[PDB]
Structures are given as structure tokens and as C-alpha cells.
Image (cartoon, rainbow over all chains, first blue to last red; front, side):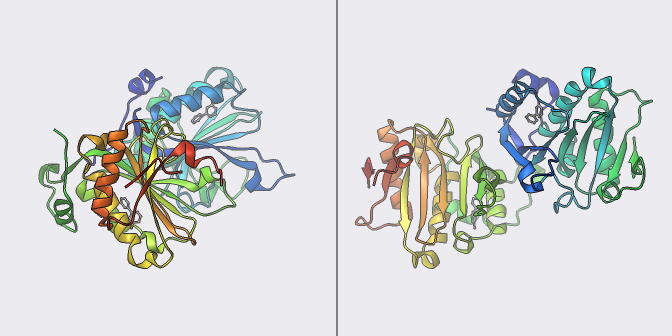
Length: 198
Length: 204
Ligand SMILES: Oc1cccc(-c2ccccc2)c1
Ligand SMILES: Oc1cccc(-c2ccccc2)c1
């Protein structure tokens, strides 16, 4: 009693009410410059059970989901999906970049696997370091990221990265980078440096 | 058997500093509970303004959260705190609230300093302590609305038509608040509260 509520992938998929450890908020953003950033960022919904997750997931999937210049974000209740939030400003993200061909084959499965890591508390005590996840749907290639709260907590960040990579099913040859938000916020060429790789 | 704690027991577990030896030293609750907060920030939608603070399922974890948090008396008007059983949202259109209602007490502006904190704590101890015997299963949660015109504390129950459960909870709640017989609490269905018409099914 006082124990973390943890669900594995098989359990979550069998529910497709069971309470979640955290309440989560789904956000939607399109950078439309005729409107201000507060108008463009929309809270879609909040949930705190497995069944309510699945009802929301099924409904968004039936709405031409993952639109072609939009971002979707799932964050713990009380964290805005912007790096300047108190819970994100000292943090960073594990980033998965998908090439054009992978929009057809991997984007849908990889976004779902990320969401199940978050809601299922798959990183043991290091799940407390997770803030949320973001998918950026773009013509040049889609990006999926897990955002974490403290870019100097090496042991939390690397455990999250390695469990995440395992849950995505990526081969050991494919390496993924963690970028500090402070480094991503400064545009310095084609790429941002990786604080860590796994 | 139902896990029931009286007021004296809960109050003895407070500020304890007990060694939770073997993770078996805490006193389990019958239910897991979630504390919610609603902020008055009208620039955001009400959905963005409802936040889950924390969940707990032992007496000692209740007290650690209670001790940490800001008191109701100190909330800016327009804020709400709610304690609900895990899996029930503190909104009337939740499946577990839509056919139910609440026992409501309203406090005047001066009772904020004298009675609001004490009534809110006594309500929380009724909930976590399962003080309504088998009828505790009809309890969804409790809400405190801090407002300029006068504060409101309510116990929400799941089913209007369970007359005996609703009336027993009302009578026990009034006793635990210490209200004189002359001051009454009223029960209103959520469906009736939701319609502004100018509505107590029961009073005790
Ligand atoms: O098909 C989609 C596309 C974008 C977001 C989601 C989603 C639904 C519920 C919770 C979290 C994310 C589903
Ligand atoms: O001082 C307060 C103010 C508002 C809520 C609470 C609370 C704390 C723990 C469980 C339930 C309610 C305490």
C-alpha cells in the first residue's frame, strides 16, 4: 500500500475501470501564425484510467489522426507541453526520427508503444522523471520524443532511453539521442547535439 | 470485513513518524482516494483548470498530503478541492455521479475563518474512515467550494433512489459535523442542481 500502479503492454492491450498512476492530458498544436500560441495550443482531453485512454485513442484514430503539420502531446496533468514549463525547463527528450517510408509502416505503432510506456509507468521509479511525449507530424519526416524533467539525472535518463528503445523494438545498431531542451532551443545548424546516446 | 476507522484512531495516526517496518506499518484504507483541485483561471477552459493533485490509500499518506497542502480557508475564491474514490471524476456527469446527488452545507463569509477548515477535515475523515457502515459504498467523494459569497461543503453519493443509504449518510454526516438539530443539511439530486429554475428532496 503506497505502491506504484504499473501495467505491462499485454494488460493494457487486454483492456482494449483500471486506474492509472497519473492523470494525463492530450494536447494538440498547429503553428498557425494568424493566431497567437495560446490560441493554437489546445487541450483535447484528460484521463486517468486505462479504459478512458482507450476510448480517447479510438476516437482520435477515427478523425484522420496525426495530421500533416501538427503536433500531439501527452503530458502529466499540470505540465504544459512547452519546454519553458517548470517541469521541462531543466530537462530534455529522447528523440526517434522517422524517415518518409516509415510514416506508412512505423508511425502509428511507435506512437502507441510510446503512449503505453507513459500510462503504464514502464520505467519503474524513473517513471517519475517522465513529463510526457510528443509526436511531430511533418512532410520531411516525423519525430516522436519522450520528454523528461532533469537532463543531469544520467541514471534516470539512460534507463528510460534503454527501456524505451527495447519497447520500440529497435535493433542495437540503431542509436537514439537525448537532447537538452536548452540546446534544442538554440538553432545552430542542421542538428542539435546529444547529451546522451543509447 | 470493511476497514473502518473512527475519528479518534485517525487523529492518533497523524504526525506519527512511525517506522514503516517491512512496508507493513501503515494503516490501509478501504478505498484508494484522489485529491483534486480546480483553479479560478478563467483564461483557461474549466477542463484545463481541473487538476489531480495526488492519490493515497493509507491513513499515514492521507496525513502527509493533508499536512503539506494549502488550507481551504487560504484558497482564493473560485477554487474547489475534491476528494473522490479512485476512478470517479469530481463532476456530476461521471457515470458514478450522474444518477446521484449531494448533502450540502453552506457557510457564511465569517464562518470561513472559524468553521471551514474544521468542517472540511471532519468530512475527509468520514470518507476515508468509512463512517457510514455498508452505506459507505454509496459515497463517491466530497467537495469544498471556496467562494466570496459563502463556502459550500458537500458529500456526493452515487444513487438518488437508494433512499435508506442517502438518509443514513445525511444523518451520520450531520452528527459528525456537530451541527445543532436546528441547522439543517439538504440533499439535492445533481440532475436538479444542473437546471437553474429560480430543490431539496431530503433535509436532516
Ligand atoms: O490516433 C491518435 C493520434 C494522436 C493522439 C492520440 C492519443 C489519444 C489518446 C491519448 C494519447 C494520444 C491518438
Ligand atoms: O488543507 C487542505 C486543503 C484542501 C484539501 C486538503 C486535503 C488533503 C488531503 C486529502 C484530502 C484533502 C487539505
